[PDB]
Image (tube, coloured by chain):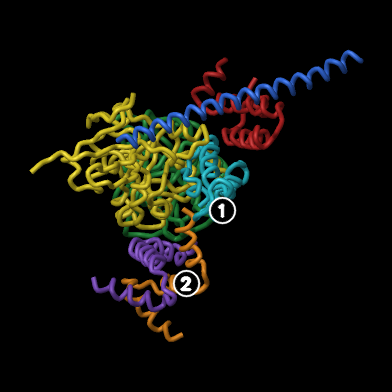
Chain colours: A green, B red, C cyan, D orange, E purple, F blue, G yellow
Amino acid sequence: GRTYCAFSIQQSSKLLGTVVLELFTDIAPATCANFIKYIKDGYQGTPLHRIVPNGWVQGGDIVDGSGKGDPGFVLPDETYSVKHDAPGVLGMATGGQPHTANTQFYISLSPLPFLDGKRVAFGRVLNKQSLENLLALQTLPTFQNERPVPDVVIASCHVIYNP
Amino acid sequence: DYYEVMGLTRSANDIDIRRAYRRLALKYHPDINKDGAAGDEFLRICEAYEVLCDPKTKGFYDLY
Amino acid sequence: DYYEVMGLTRSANDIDIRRAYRRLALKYHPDINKDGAAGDEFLRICEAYEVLCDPKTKGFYDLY
Amino acid sequence: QTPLYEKMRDYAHSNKVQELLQKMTADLFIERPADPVTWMIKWLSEEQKR
Amino acid sequence: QTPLYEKMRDYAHSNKVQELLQKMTADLFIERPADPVTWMIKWLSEEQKR
Amino acid sequence: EAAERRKLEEKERRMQQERERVERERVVRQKVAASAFARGYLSGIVNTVFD
Amino acid sequence: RYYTPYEVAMHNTPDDCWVSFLGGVYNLTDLIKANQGALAAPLIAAAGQDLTHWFDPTTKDPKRHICPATHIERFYTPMGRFIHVPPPEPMCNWDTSFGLPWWRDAKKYQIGLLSARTRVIRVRNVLTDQEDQIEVPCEEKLVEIRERYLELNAHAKSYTWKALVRTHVFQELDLNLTLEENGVPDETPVFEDHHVPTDYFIPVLHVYWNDDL
């Protein structure tokens, strides 16, 4: 009964895959509201910034697109209830100190016990095709200091199944 | 065989492989453990982890 | 430091430490080097080699 | 070599200088001034009385 | 690692104060005054003039 | 110039002496090892003979 | 050119920071100037130091390991997190727009080249007797030995050099051949291996005057 949203991953005019996500609109409502408002207006051409091999696929900066903070809003810390234990746990990222969250988001690619209680996790991947798309995105031909050498970009992004 | 020397079930996450290597190596290192049996066991563990860490070599061995 | 007194660098090998201590403790031994500013120097040479000739103490010092 | 360092180690690890420097640094971090040099001039001036 | 501690570390490790401290302590371990409180005052006064 | 040439010749003579010293040190170490090992193995051999 | 380790040691301050690693001498001053925080601490604290132990030979990046806490491979930074090292966890301030790590950006942050060994030359000015020991890299052409010695005599260019080449006769030395090509060997390893003090004999370079006007 939750909300759903999908987006595509493309590297240098080559469609690399698509992913669909379920949003925990019953656990952390305000974070989902901000995330959908920004996926409706934003994220349309924002690169995948940071990619850790056995860690997480990160990205989603807006005003810069290359990993520095943005003005215009700050998001408070909602809830540490969803526990990072399985791959494909979408969440928001902030500085070391809480209540500074921004559009920067991250999807886990392995059990991440340390993150529990430090990062707001409010979503999940839905199927195995999307998770395999991320796991394949790990082994790009060349990526320099944790950034893909070409621009791995969100070409399209949309919301399906709910208001 | 390789998964047997570390007690791996051919269905375990890479994290468990890393924990197996760390635990067995730090218990079986030639320096920390003055034991020739420990030395050859550590050699076996090193070779097994070296051939079990790389995903390309992982698939190449799994097809065997 | 325990390193600069031997003259070595932070990346010295084991043979490097052997050679450094060899020359520095054959240059400053009381029976060979009659006198001078060689009182503290020999003691720190001995202490540095004693700390750095054993891997457990060497590593514990290196981290702290 | 040992003699040059020892002459400075013996001076610097003696109480007066060390627990002067530590308190000065502590108060400098607490105050957070724009220009540290005149602040240290002041602090040493009103500490010279003590 | 509260925001104060991080802010203090940023100020403590800044260029100005750290280089000034390094310079002052080097000079002080050169001259070695038996009354560093006053020698620091004169040294900082002459530095500030530039 | 003559002083310098004499000093260099003296250094060469000292180095020849040191090479001789190292050689005889190695030889005496080999002698003592080849006596100790011989005794320590003939001991086991004669023990086996008694057995 | 080249630099002895002591010469690298002369620059240890946030105003002039030099580091030697993997055989290269780097002037990281503009880094510390542009990145002034807790990130710059671990290399400020090792200004003028030898930084080769941080890195590994096979690749130019620092050593890596499996982090015990998160079990994700990342740089081994016992000293602390130096500039251009990612944070362990997903943050919102570590940008990756910058081009290359400073240990890979040789063209912009490398000056000279660190000497793998040094030797002691005893220079003797024959006209006015003035002995002088000096340390120079063991692999350097006589032109830069003359450049080092220019701080002893401001008129060393006019002077002519000579060495006890092999019997043994004081003969001329070509400037573009290093001290080893010219026939001045290095014997400190043999000195050490044979228990002879490394300050017992030193090779000597005579420096005669060449009349000018």
Q: Position of residue G124 (x, y in %)?
A: 29, 42
Identify the residue at image location x=46%, y=43%. C9
Residue A81 badge = 1
Q: Position of residue A41 (x, y in %)?
A: 31, 49
Residue A22 in sight here: no
Q: Nearer the viewer, residue C8 or F9?
A: F9
> Pointer 2 indicates a residue of which chain?
D
Residue at the top extreme, as displayed: F49
Residue F2 sits in quarter: top left
Amino acid type at circle 2 is Val
Identify the residue at image location x=43%, y=55%. A95
Residue G179 sits in quarter: top left
- Above or below for D17 versus A134: below
Q: Secondary structure at mark 2?
A: helix
Q: Position of residue B53 (x, y in %)?
A: 54, 28
Q: Nearer the viewer, residue A117 or D43?
A: D43
- Above or below for D23 versus G143: below
Identify the residue at image location x=30%, y=76%. E45
Residue at the left extreme, as displayed: G213
Residue D17 badge = 2
* Horizontal arrangement in the rendering, residue G146 relative to residue C29 (left or right): left
Q: Residues within 10 Å of mark 2 (few under 14, many from 20)?
A: many
Amino acid type at circle 1 is Ser
Q: CA distance from mark 2 to mark 1?
A: 53 Å
- Check contact, mark 2 vs mark 1: CB within 8 A: no
Residue C19 in sight here: yes
Total labels drawn: 2
Q: Position of residue B21 (x, y in %)?
A: 62, 33
